[PDB]
Amino acid sequence: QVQLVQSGAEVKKPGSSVKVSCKVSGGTFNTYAIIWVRQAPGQGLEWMGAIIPFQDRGQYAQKFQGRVTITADKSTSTAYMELSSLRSEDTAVYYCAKESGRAVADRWGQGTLVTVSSGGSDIVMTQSPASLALSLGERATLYCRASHSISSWLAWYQQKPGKAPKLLIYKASTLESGVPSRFSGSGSGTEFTLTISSLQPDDFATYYCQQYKSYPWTFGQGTKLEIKR
Amino acid sequence: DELDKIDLSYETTESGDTAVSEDSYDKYASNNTNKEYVCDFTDQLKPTESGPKVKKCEVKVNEPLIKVKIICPLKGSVEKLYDNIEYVPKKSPYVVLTKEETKLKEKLLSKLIYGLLISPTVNEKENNFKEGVIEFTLPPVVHKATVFYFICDNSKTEDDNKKGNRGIVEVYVEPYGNKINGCAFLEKIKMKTFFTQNIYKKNNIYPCYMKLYSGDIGGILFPKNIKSTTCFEEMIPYNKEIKWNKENKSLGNLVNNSVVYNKEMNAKYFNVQYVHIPTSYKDTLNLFCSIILKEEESNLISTSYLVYVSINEG
């Protein structure tokens, strides 16, 4: 199947630049978008930009305009993200991901830790509850609200500590292949739900909703679902 | 116009509702014969127990003047098997799909590829999937890599436990060529960079020169106000290589196996003709034709253009 392998951890001085690589194997490279997402430690996911390799030009969140360059080398099926003028707040795990014909980013790299050591009209995603404490075998219900109508262009991701986001649901209610049927999604427009019919030990994690109607893609701040004490 | 009005709100994806990812598409190349690249879905989308699969016909172009032909079976063309087939865009080939962000959205094909030739008809029927097939001819030159799509989706057709397949055409045009030997008689920047010679409006008899060799492509962007032209059905040879039958006047008559593209000048958008000198033709031939303009708005002076075509003048 398809694998995204990123370059390894980096330590940089403030003011420096860093370039992270993302090698795609087993999937078509030239005509599918590669996106870059970063996650400051203990914080949420943040879309930085994307590139469709044949176009030879990336698109970027205004937040990073002028500091990020995304490129793609078609002969090696490797995408790159270069972030300049690094500062402490840029310390984060940087992820590459790609879409596979279903609009959603459904294949993710393993992440690259980068350590720094010496806009209006964007769609806001609001998740609740911020934390859920439940016992094994109980049902969990998670909620996601969008500030603008996104029809059904909403995905749900599961993230375990230290691991890349894993797609569970896309198009609001479609299960990704291999995802157990106890996960289900509902809603369209501005209100969405993720339900886990019966919690199992593997299900304890942080869950994120993401609108992929329009760039910049935006994530909710996540629901942390942990075991009842 | 109604042939090519685009719905900016239209949205879809390559996979549609099939839930199949691209690494699991059944990918295959178009069947290419001479300069016609054909994607034929007549037998690819019938329902099977395994359905719906995604059938992706890959059209890869890095040569000039390729004709792309796409055949999508018609609803009811065979009982039951295509009762719910849809094709997208409805106004293909004038409107195509391109990837914006990560979804497929409508795009004017003529805005994507300058000089592309869409004839009004195919097999003496409308050039539209409603008649079962669409065709277009890519130009002699393309500056930027370009990717666009057509959908012929039978996945909503059900017959017993079986479902039809979703057909995709991906046309991937890599850059090829530089500049067409010939003249453009003068969005506008696309016009000015496409031909080796630009003839800007003059009020006299002015000469365009098209110098060609075996295998070369030439062409002309004819003036807006054209009234009449003998290019290229009524050429006059000059210089006395061989004896001339005066009825052998078309480039076809004079250069065996030469091809003229858009002879009828009926393609939409682009007032162009392209000519291809075959590699087989090694003889030297100097030819002449003319372009006459309408005096719709007078400048007090009439405009005409002399076109000189020299073949293998080495």
Image (cartoon, rainbow, N blue to C red):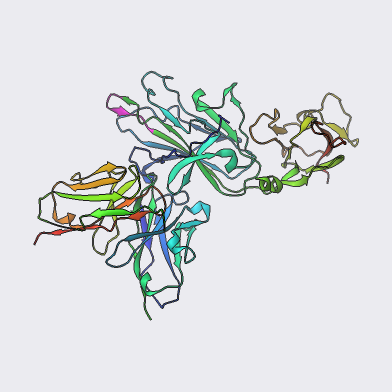
- Residue A165 lies, in percent from the top left, at 29, 57
Q: Is residue B77 above or below residue A105?
A: above
Q: Say left or right for A35 vs B242.
A: left
Q: Which residues are magenta?
A: B159-165
Q: Nearer the viewer, residue B205 or A144?
A: A144
Residue depicted at x 65% and y 31% = B267
Residue farthest to the top, as pictured: B79
Image-quadrant location for residue B313: top right
Label count reads 0
Q: Nearer the viewer, residue B280 or A177?
A: A177
Image-quadrant location for residue B287: top right
Q: Say left or right for B134 vs A4.
A: right
Q: Is residue B168 above or below residue A59?
A: above
Q: Is residue B219 above or below residue A148?
A: above
Residue B164 on the magenta span: yes
Q: Say left or right for B25 vs B300.
A: left
Residue B58 in view:
no
Q: Quadrant where the C terminus of chain A lies? A: bottom left
- Residue B211 lies, in percent from the top left, at 79, 43
Residue B305 on the magenta span: no
- Residue B309 lies, in percent from the top left, at 81, 39
Q: Nearer the viewer, residue B286 or B13?
A: B13
Residue farthest to the right, as pictured: B240
- Residue B293 lies, in percent from the top left, at 80, 32
Residue depicted at x 42% and y 64% = A21
Q: Is residue A90 above or below residue B132?
A: below
Residue B159 in view:
yes
Image-quadrant location for residue A80: bottom left
Residue farthest to the front, as pictured: A120
